[PDB]
Length: 111
Image (cartoon, rainbow, N blue to C red):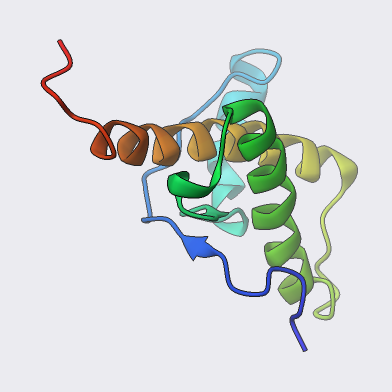
């Protein structure tokens, strides 16, 4: 059924970054509703990427879209504004989760 991913690696749940988007008007607006977005991110292992600019843009498609292909049948959907807010956060979350593993792949004693 849900043949979009195939079987990507699902990251840990996190607290989300709050973000301004455009200002502290939207910051609270986002936090008031933020439950509809993911707590984690979908991507492959870091062992199967080359640069964040391709990782994150994919991660930001895939995670959103796997949230979409769950809510889309409910009568929920997302507005293009909610896709915008989601992709905003999900970009940061992708970058956060990868950064964990990116340094875990290495971790010489980076200072």
